[PDB]
Image (tube, coloured by chain):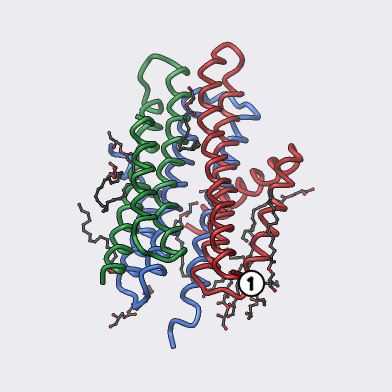
Chain colours: A blue, B green, C red
Amino acid sequence: AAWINEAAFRQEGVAVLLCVVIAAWLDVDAVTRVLLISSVMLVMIVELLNSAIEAVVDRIGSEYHELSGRAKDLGSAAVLIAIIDAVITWAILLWSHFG
Amino acid sequence: AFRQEGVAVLLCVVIAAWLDVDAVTRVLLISSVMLVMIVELLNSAIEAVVDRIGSEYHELSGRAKDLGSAAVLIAIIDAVITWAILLWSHFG
Amino acid sequence: GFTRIIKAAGYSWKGLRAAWINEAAFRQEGVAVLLCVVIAAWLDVDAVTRVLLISSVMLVMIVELLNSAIEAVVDRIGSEYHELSGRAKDLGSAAVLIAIIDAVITWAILLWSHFG
Ligand SMILES: CCCCCCC/C=C/CCCCCC(=O)OC[C@@H](O)CO
Ligand SMILES: CCCCCCC/C=C\CCCCCC(=O)OC[C@@H](O)CO
Ligand SMILES: CCCCCCC/C=C\CCCCCC(=O)OC[C@@H](O)CO
Ligand SMILES: CCCCCCC/C=C\CCCCCC(=O)OC[C@@H](O)CO
Ligand SMILES: CCCCCCC/C=C\CCCCCC(=O)OC[C@@H](O)CO
Ligand SMILES: CCCCCCC/C=C\CCCCCC(=O)OC[C@@H](O)CO
Ligand SMILES: CCCCCCC/C=C\CCCCCC(=O)OC[C@@H](O)CO
Ligand SMILES: CCCCCCC/C=C\CCCCCC(=O)OC[C@@H](O)CO
Ligand SMILES: CCCCCCC/C=C\CCCCCC(=O)OC[C@@H](O)CO
Ligand SMILES: CCCCCCC/C=C\CCCCCC(=O)OC[C@@H](O)CO
Ligand SMILES: CCCCCCC/C=C\CCCCCC(=O)OC[C@@H](O)CO
Ligand SMILES: CCCCCCC/C=C\CCCCCC(=O)OC[C@@H](O)CO
């Protein structure tokens, strides 16, 4: 409900969205296509969960606590691992596809 | 309801075993369903925190539940795309 | 932008570092994950199987980190509200254990079909 109107989410969304379109056009087999799409959708999923966690922390207050920062650091780490999994997925699958 | 969610899993698992597909297709079909559960469980956990922070509404209280529900939505969508693509290929 | 990434990549490193430093269980988990990838990378399998073997154990790490974040929130709130902090932790722990089960099963089935 109107969270999709922030810049960072739009660039993240459009990046993921763009990959799904690309994956939908590539001449690959079904299992590869599913994996190409799954890897980038997971990034969007995890980022949504990371932002959701961040919302809960900011909800509590602006006064800083060590665990408040750590929850955000762990959420970011989850996204990073997701992004790496996506790059690796496309790397392994689309290697030697152009030729 | 996780009660119906659990039976929904079994049905997908039963169908997955029913169809004459190889191990890779079988792992993809079921994992996608399992990812929904994981995200839902994670979303439900986030919700449990929000609800005890306060019984009041806040800009950030409801913003979390939306982003969490969005994550579940994206997971369910990915699951449908997977079952569509694979079954289409299987019955090609 | 380019500077958003440096800032976000920095929080990620603090996340992984703090998670590593604070628990032996996490360190041993990261080792188990790291090995599994190395093994997956060297196996003589097709590209989709390779990705499946890698992708799954990665998901374990992802869910682990997300859950650890959620745990940090309920500990932040304090002792008083504990009981629904308990349910949030129970839910998140289910997500972690499910993901690990999926990883274990996936590796079993796939390595079975290949070596068998
Ligand atoms: C920084 C050095 C390591 C970086 C590794 C990243 C890309 C390489 C991945 C593994 C390639 C090394 C050979 C292992 C392997 O894949 O065996 C498969 C074999 O069937 C043909 O290569
Ligand atoms: C209610 C709207 C839901 C989405 C609208 C319909 C989308 C059409 C198909 C579902 C996913 C297709 C994505 C993959 C694709 O385009 O390749 C198709 C081809 O691989 C079939 O094997
Ligand atoms: C500066 C623009 C960057 C664009 C993003 C990168 C583009 C990636 C791939 C471009 C080619 C699209 C795939 C076309 C293709 O493989 O053909 C599919 C097959 O059905 C042809 O009959
Ligand atoms: C080796 C060839 C790879 C070809 C491209 C594969 C890219 C796959 C996934 C990357 C898309 C991630 C989109 C989300 C994103 O970047 O936002 C996260 C970050 O900007 C927020 O801090
Ligand atoms: C185009 C951008 C590249 C981005 C960097 C990707 C680094 C991460 C993982 C590297 C794994 C790719 C190699 C996998 C592979 O298929 O080996 C090559 C082999 O198929 C050729 O015989
Ligand atoms: C021969 C086997 C096919 C017969 C069709 C019977 C289908 C029965 C159950 C299908 C799976 C149940 C769970 C899937 C599901 O609920 O997806 C809905 C999803 O959009 C979440 O609302
Ligand atoms: C060919 C028949 C099988 C179709 C399988 C398609 C898989 C789609 C979704 C899999 C996950 C099921 C999750 C069910 C769910 O969360 O719905 C419950 C809720 O929406 C009802 O209020
Ligand atoms: C050899 C390594 C295997 C392939 C992975 C290579 C890494 C490629 C791109 C990663 C850089 C993007 C950094 C994204 C990031 O900072 O995450 C943001 C997140 O933590 C908070 O939104
Ligand atoms: C194969 C692609 C991803 C490979 C990594 C899989 C899991 C990701 C990270 C595992 C934990 C890395 C954190 C290491 C770290 O920060 O330790 C610092 C500490 O030892 C300093 O004393
Ligand atoms: C908690 C248990 C998780 C354990 C994590 C580390 C062990 C997991 C997988 C490693 C066992 C694979 C052994 C088979 C293998 O490596 O194939 C050999 C292949 O290269 C044939 O030459
Ligand atoms: C925390 C981030 C750490 C990132 C770790 C980097 C990932 C390392 C290896 C993943 C890529 C494996 C490439 C597999 C490969 O090259 O084998 C190709 C072989 O089949 C040739 O036919
Ligand atoms: C077949 C053996 C059981 C395996 C369980 C896996 C089934 C799939 C999803 C179940 C997740 C369990 C989450 C339910 C739960 O924890 O509720 C209890 C707790 O949250 C408060 O009562």
SS state under label 1: loop
Residue A57 horizontal side relative to residue C11, left or right = left
The residue under the point 31% across, 66% down is: A21
What residue is drawn where x is 43% and y is 66%?
Answer: B22
Q: Tell me the quarter of the picture where residue A17 sits.
A: bottom left
Residue in front for this viewpoint, B67 or C86: C86
Q: Report whether the residue tagged 1 is closer than 8 Å to ligand 10.
A: yes
Residue at 66%, 54% in the rendered image: C33
- Relative placement, left or right, of B3 versus A63 is left
Percent position of residue B6, x then y: 39, 36
- Foreground of the two, B84 or A74: B84
The amino acid type found where label 1 is placed reads: Leu
Hey, which residue is sitting farthest bottom in the picture? A99
Q: Which residue is mark 1?
A: C43
Given the image, what chain letter belongs to the residue carrying mark 1? C
x, y (%) of residue C76? 60, 23
Left or right: where C76 falls relative to B12? right
